[PDB]
Image: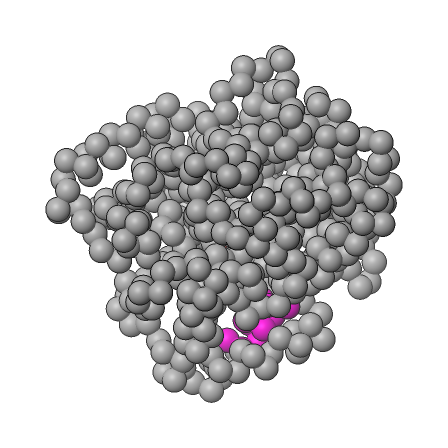
Amino acid sequence: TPPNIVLILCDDMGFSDLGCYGSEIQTPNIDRLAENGVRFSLFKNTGRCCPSRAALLTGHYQHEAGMGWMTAVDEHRPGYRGQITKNIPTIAEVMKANGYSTYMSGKWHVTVDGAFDTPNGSYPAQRGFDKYYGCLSGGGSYYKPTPVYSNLTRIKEFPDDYYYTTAITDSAVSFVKQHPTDKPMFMYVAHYAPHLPLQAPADRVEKCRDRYKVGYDMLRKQRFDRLKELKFISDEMDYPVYQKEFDGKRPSWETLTPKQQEQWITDMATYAAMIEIVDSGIGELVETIKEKGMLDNTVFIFLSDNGATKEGGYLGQLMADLSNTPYRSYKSQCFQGGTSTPFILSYGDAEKNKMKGQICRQPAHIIDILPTCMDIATATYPSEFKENLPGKSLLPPIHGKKIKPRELYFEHQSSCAIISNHWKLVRGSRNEPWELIDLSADPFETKDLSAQYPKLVKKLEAKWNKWAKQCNVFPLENKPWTERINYYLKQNPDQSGI
Ligand SMILES: CC(=O)N[C@@H]1[C@@H](O)[C@H](O[C@@H]2O[C@H](CO)[C@H](O)[C@H](O)[C@H]2O)[C@@H](CO)O[C@@H]1O
Ligand SMILES: [Ca+2]
């Protein structure tokens, strides 16, 4: 059979949150996949949950798939349907067409929020997955997610010790146990952790608490120094302290009150525990693949949907500053902090890892997941659809072939970016000017060159506008969350996603 693929996606995890990307968070099972396999330094995602999940599932830019913004509202306009289109197959439908058994555990977040009570054609088990267990929602608690579905069956009752991360791991383990080993398996594990709220069993929090007592300044510099030791960042690079995003008043650890420090420690220890429990679960899933005799014919892939968030509030922004090290800004904008993710690709067969323990510096985007999975599987695109995938297989550069130049596109809430070769043109919103960043010299986006290269600003801006028009990105929208939902509910309260 062609190789099994286990595709693991964490939620709002920052660039340096894994041990193998310089973390104080202990991720021994993920780090072992990295040691066996390859880590990417320049893998980017969209900056937000629903767009990243649409792009991952389709291999297309988010607006082409109908998810320019979020499942919170269907805007009833091209690019912004709050839901993945029927008109582009998902990775599950592609793998199924090539004889794969398809399983998904965890967070979907590409079905319109108004369609949570009855399947509307966009549910996981209607879009290529033979088995699904998880919550369709992008939000909610670890103790009672809603709505939870087993395929198309609504689950209303939960055992008294329910924890969503544990249920995701246990459902994935159960799918592998039941998997007929004469068939290839495609397994998507969409973890909720470390998405808010901050919830974890007390023993795992207390296991993490001590290391956070030193505060974020000591921990953040230590992550930076580990990123140099690990060869993610050149020895000469200065430790970046970001002031712009804190309105010029970034509070040093010593500036917080005792009560604020104690709350930051508890919050970050809880965040760490949430990731450690995912890592324990990855351990369990790897153990199950071994027991089933599947390891030597399995490929593991790990990434995050978007950078760490400041949505938790003031102390949450300081958590996200630490998590996104060395990069600026957060989830929901197109700077490096919101868009940079770890990316690991690990063959269970040691001999199939041609860059064992190394970093691959191929620039890449979450659109690359589907063509990479099709290359692993020697899979053909379903014959009823024209194959127009904009992304690239990432297999050639980890099998010794030369890095290829990329042109990558970003938009979220009128935050916009194009990466073209070593250049990044980026804006925080339509209310902020384009900034031109030389990523080769200035990966932390600290020095705007736009005044120095006005012709290049114009060329990159024109490339971005051509992409945006072609992908149904326009018009841009930046109304904040509640105002935006109310506006489009008023325009058209049909949130059925039919
Ligand atoms: C109640 C309310 O209006 N809160 C909103 C948040 O929902 C929103 O955060 C997003 O929430 C969705 C919910 O499915 C996902 O959890 C997503 O990951 C979040 O980005 C934020 C956005 O800034 O605004 C309010 O807090
Ligand atoms: Ca997310």
Is-magenta flag for residue 304? no
At a point 38% along the width and 84% down the height, the residue shown is: 254
Is-magenta flag for residue 266? yes
Of 220 and 317, the residue lying toward us: 220
At a point 50% along the width and 25% down the height, the residue shown is: 389
Q: Is residue 121 visible?
A: no
The picture quadrant where one finds residue 328 is bottom left
Position of residue 131 in the picture relative to residue 136 (left or right): right
Q: Which residues are magenta?
A: 264-273
Q: Position of residue 67 (x, y in %)?
A: 49, 34
Please determine whether, in this image, residue 489 is positioned above or below residue 35: above
Q: Is residue 4 visible?
A: yes
Please determine whether, in this image, residue 61 is positioned above or below residue 362: above
Q: Position of residue 184 (x, y in %)?
A: 76, 32
Of 81 and 408, the residue lying toward us: 408
Looking at the image, the residue that sits furthest to the top is 384
| Quadrant of the image containing the C terminus | top right
At a point 68% along the width and 48% down the height, the residue shown is: 350
The picture quadrant where one finds residue 246 is bottom left
Q: Position of residue 485 (x, y in %)?
A: 47, 42
Position of residue 188 in the picture relative to residue 304 (left or right): right
Q: Position of residue 325 (x, y in %)?
A: 42, 63
| Quadrant of the image containing the N terminus | top right
